[PDB]
Image (cartoon, rainbow, N blue to C red; front, side):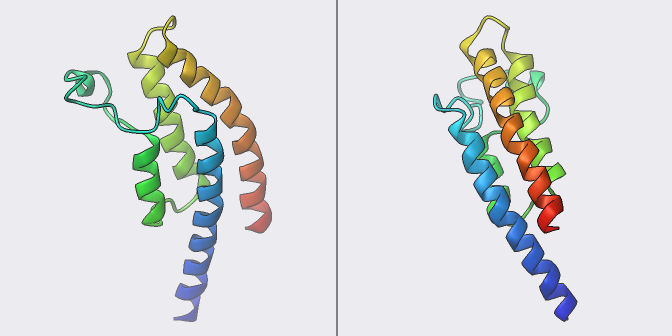
Amino acid sequence: SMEQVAMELRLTELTRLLRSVLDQLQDKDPARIFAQPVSLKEVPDYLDHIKHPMDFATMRKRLEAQGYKNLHEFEEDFDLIIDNCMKYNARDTVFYRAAVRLRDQGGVVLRQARREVDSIG
């Protein structure tokens, strides 16, 4: 139907906007601490601690399959990246600190993304 096409165009345009959001958030991680999944070869106990691992590459895979239906879903996955790290790693670590800085800097980007998603519909 034409309605199904229109909906698909909206999803494609959301995907476009989320791709730009993803790029901007990932620039706030110049160390690339969050770029890839935590390695279970290198942290074999990880899944005992963290039940829903997340990372920027995994988000990018979902994004390119048009797998985020709305900004809330995308924000859920970004918050997982941050929150997983702040639980597994202690406060005094470069990992925890990187997550705090990513959260703080990402807030700015996400605040305007929400306005754009509501604004453009």
